[PDB]
Length: 235
Ligand SMILES: *[C@@H]1O[C@H](CO)[C@@H](O)[C@H](O)[C@H]1NC(C)=O
Ligand SMILES: O[C@@H]1[C@@H](O)[C@H](O)OC[C@H]1O
Ligand SMILES: [Cl-]
Ligand SMILES: [Cl-]
Ligand SMILES: [Cl-]
Ligand SMILES: [Cl-]
Ligand SMILES: [Cl-]
Ligand SMILES: [Cl-]
Ligand SMILES: [Cl-]
Ligand SMILES: [Cl-]
Ligand SMILES: [Cl-]
Ligand SMILES: [Cl-]
Ligand SMILES: [Cu+2]
Image (spheres, rainbow, N blue to C red):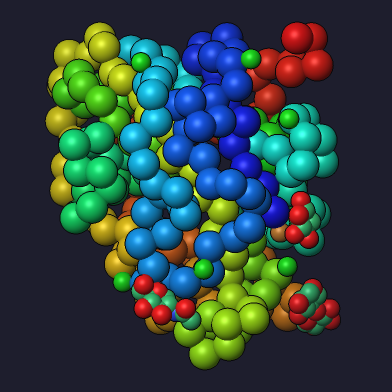
């Protein structure tokens, strides 16, 4: 159980974004149904009144939390990968529009899943804003907790992979559009019961064997990291 509080741009807190520039759900419950419209932007997908201004090459940092800001973030049991997608705002997230900007599953050197590192990062993970057309966008951050992913939700609705999905409204002002956005995948639709990384046993299969669900990261993407960029406690 986890939610987004807000974002930072180039290491500068943009402030509490909940129901303001984040299309926040009312609580931190996971989405499990792969076929639900809730896969798009969680259970309350609607236009919220602000959109965060950024330029290509900026560092955009999602900040997650559990019950309160900068707490334990997400329960340590919730081992799994983290991805970030982008789509044009005009889509409202419908159709084949989501382009993957970032993937992190398991780090062999440190022996840590993305979620494990997100905790250590005080909930913060970033992407570098790509050189797409100026305009309004949705950035869809997705955490997949795998602690009950040995079962499929479609077969046993009390278990299943757990999706913590947050959409941020982001406006890209300065960009040369030198890497125009390509074709994306649909949510719901891209992940099915047979997709790699949706059904997995984290307890008996070595984490080095895990493969995260496709699509693969777009070649136009400019990187990201799971790492603290700002200290929330100073505010
Ligand atoms: C999953 O979502 C689909 C599409 O909305 C829906 O028809 C189905 O009833 C859902 N499954 C459960 C178990 O609620
Ligand atoms: O559902 C519970 C949620 O309310 C809390 O925030 O995190 C622990 C969960 O069990
Ligand atoms: Cl929890
Ligand atoms: Cl604030
Ligand atoms: Cl669900
Ligand atoms: Cl605005
Ligand atoms: Cl809070
Ligand atoms: Cl860190
Ligand atoms: Cl749970
Ligand atoms: Cl540019
Ligand atoms: Cl579907
Ligand atoms: Cl980064
Ligand atoms: Cu949880």
